[PDB]
Length: 45
RNA sequence: AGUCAUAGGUAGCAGAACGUUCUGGAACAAUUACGCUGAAAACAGUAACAGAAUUGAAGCUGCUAACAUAAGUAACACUAAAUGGAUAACAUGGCCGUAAGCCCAAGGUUUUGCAUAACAAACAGUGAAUACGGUU
Ligand SMILES: [Mg+2]
Ligand SMILES: [Mg+2]
Ligand SMILES: [Mg+2]
Ligand SMILES: [Mg+2]
Ligand SMILES: [Mg+2]
Ligand SMILES: [Mg+2]
Ligand SMILES: [Mg+2]
Image (spheres, rainbow, N blue to C red):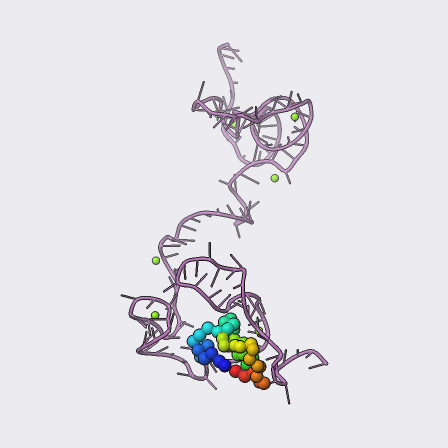
C-alpha cells in the first residue's frame, strides 16, 4: 500500500513537487496509488 | 592708386560684417560631392534680394547621455572543516542538537518537479473522506 523507498526519501514520487505532505496528500503522492482501491475511513499517514 | 594723418585698452558707447532654421519672389541638390585650397576674422567650397526668429556655448559646485581615471586596485575574514581526479549517490572526518532539527502563523505568491547541456518551459504540480482552519 506504500512505496517505502519514497517514504524514506530515497525515490521519486507521484506529484514530485510536494516533497513534504500534510495528513492528507499522503494517499495521492504515493507512487503506488491505485485509483480503483477503496478509500480508508480516516486517511492516515 | 600718389602723398600725408591716425590705429594699447577694462567698464561703457558707436559702426561694419559672418553663420544656423524657416518663408516670399514659378521651381537653386532626380542622376551626389570629391583638381585642395581660398579669405583679415567670424568662415567658405550647392544661388541671390528681402523678411520671421525657441539664431551662435570650455566657462552657471548647471541638466541628460556616453566614455575614461583611480585600477584589474579595494573587496570576495562573523561562523562548523573538509578529503578521496565530481558542489556525488559511496566511504572517511567534523559542526548544531532548546538548534543550524521538526510543525505552523504573518508575509512572499509559483520562488516548487523533470534533461550525465539541453531545443526545458512552450511541460507538470496544491484533491477535505476524521465533527482540519475560515465563512457563522
Ligand atoms: Mg583700439
Ligand atoms: Mg600706438
Ligand atoms: Mg522660394
Ligand atoms: Mg536659446
Ligand atoms: Mg587578482
Ligand atoms: Mg566532495
Ligand atoms: Mg502562506
